[PDB]
Image (tube, rainbow, N blue to C red):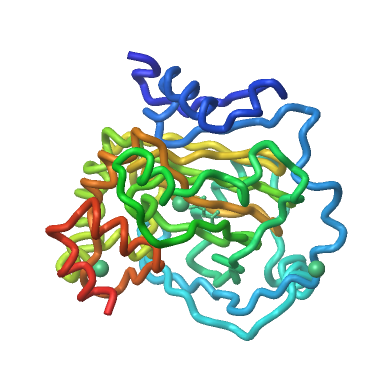
């Protein structure tokens, strides 16, 4: 078995190898990459997502989110308070203000220490989940707006044609902006490209050990656990590496820099934070190997998780017994 310790693997495809996206995913899996839950892909040196980022300041962040924490430094939840709209140029200035800027630090490890020590005492503002793309239309390789759609994958594998579309999302971050512990909707893959700015640190649990994280989360968030049988689908809970190590949960960490891709694999729990002002683009995708994970994916039916139009068909076809109850949650 390849990669039996479930380490995060880093790949350096040549420009020739960067042509065929599906084939490269299947190659990474042949080397065991999926066992970690997360992989890094450094694009060939000839490749570019677009020519420059010089003209992005007029993109609108219609609903910036202020991420307010409750709990203790290593075990907390966050809620998102909606703020007034602002442009990316306004948000960048805010991120660089004395109130919100990255503190002085020695290296990524010192910054990580400061994040875990101090995150809860601040409320950074995140421009998340903005439909759109920063890939130039002429970029032919690994263009996250030109991938094969999950609806077409389901149709190719299972023969059933379904409604729904699959488009990317932009994320504008600042120091301490946080993504809570989660897997993707329907335990899909994700791919994330860091277009510009400061790094993003990731934490991940191997898929084969995801239920260990879930059991710890039920112990640490006991009221949330009683409220919903899949409350990590709310995307609000944080647990530090120190707490994970104290409780024997297997995980790995890695920092993504501008110009790098990350891939998350089905049922790979992940969480992380941004080091300073940045912009990422991400989208879900599927392969044949995903279908069995989609069939088994947990669902939130309490009503909190509230997700896309396109998830309907996935539940209806892959999880017909759950369909009924899950849709009660969504309406
Ligand atoms: O970048 C972020 O805030 C969160 N992204 C992801 O969870 C992802 O790409 O799967
Ligand atoms: Mg603009
Ligand atoms: Ni994710
Ligand atoms: Zn729920």
On screen, residue 110 versus residue 237, left or right, reads right
The x and y percentages for residue 294 are 28, 46
- As drawn, the residue found furthest toward the top would be 1
What residue lies at 38% left-to-right and 47% top-to-bottom? 188
In this orientation, does residue 74 appear? no
The x and y percentages for residue 191 are 53, 44
Q: Quadrant of residue 323?
A: bottom left
What residue lies at 64% left-to-right and 22% top-to-bottom? 17
The x and y percentages for residue 259 are 71, 40
Q: Is residue 84 above or below residue 253?
A: below
What residue lies at 43% left-to-right and 34% top-to-bottom? 252
User: Looking at the image, how many numbered discs can be counted on the residues?
Assistant: 0
The x and y percentages for residue 96 are 76, 66
What residue lies at 68% left-to-right and 40% top-to-bottom? 107
On screen, residue 163 versus residue 212, left or right, reads right
Q: Nearer the viewer, residue 180 or 221?
A: 180
| Quarter of image, ligand 4 | bottom left
On screen, residue 95 versus residue 222, left or right, reads right
On screen, residue 90 versus residue 133, left or right, reads right
Q: Nearer the viewer, residue 127 or 152?
A: 152
Q: Nearer the viewer, residue 165 or 89?
A: 165
Q: Nearer the viewer, residue 148 or 31?
A: 148
Q: Quadrant of residue 306?
A: bottom left
């Amino acid at each position: 078995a390849q990669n039996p310790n479930c380490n995060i693997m880093i790949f350096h495809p040549t420009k020739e190898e960067f042509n065929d996206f599906d084939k490269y995913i299947a190659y990474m899996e042949s080397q065991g990459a999926h066992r970690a839950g997360l992989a890094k892909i450094i694009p060939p040196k000839e490749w570019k997502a677009r020519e420059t980022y010089d003209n992005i300041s007029e993109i609108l962040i219609a609903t910036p989110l202020q991420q307010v924490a409750s709990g203790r430094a290593g075990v907390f939840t966050q809620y998102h308070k909606k703020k007034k709209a602002m442009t990316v140029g306004e948000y960048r200035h805010l991120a660089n203000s004395k109130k919100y800027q990255t503190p002085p630090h020695q290296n990524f490890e010192d910054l990580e220490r400061k994040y875990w020590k101090n995150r809860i005492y601040n409320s950074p503002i995140y421009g998340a989940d903005i439909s759109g793309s920063l890939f130039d239309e002429n970029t032919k390789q690994w263009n996250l707006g030109h991938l094969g759609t999950i609806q077409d994958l389901l149709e190719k594998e299972c023969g059933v044609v379904i409604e729904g579309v699959n488009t990317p999302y932009l994320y504008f971050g600042m120091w301490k902006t946080t993504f809570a512990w989660h897997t993707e909707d329907m335990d899909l893959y994700s791919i994330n490209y860091l277009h510009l700015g400061e790094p993003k640190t990731w934490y991940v649990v191997p898929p084969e050990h995801g239920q260990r994280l879930e059991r710890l989360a039920r112990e640490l968030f006991p009221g949330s656990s009683r409220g919903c049988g899949a409350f990590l689908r709310h995307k609000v809970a944080l647990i530090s590496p120190t707490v994970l190590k104290e409780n024997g949960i297997p995980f790995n960490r890695i920092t993504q820099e501008a110009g790098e891709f990350m891939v998350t694999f089905p049922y790979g729990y992940h969480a992380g934070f941004n080091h300073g002002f940045n912009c990422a683009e991400a989208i879900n995708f599927a392969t044949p190997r995903w279908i069995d994970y989609g069939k088994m994916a947990s669902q939130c039916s309490c009503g909190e998780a509230r997700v896309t139009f396109s998830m309907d068909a996935f539940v209806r076809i892959l999880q017909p017994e759950r369909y009924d109850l899950w849709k009660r949650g969504q309406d």
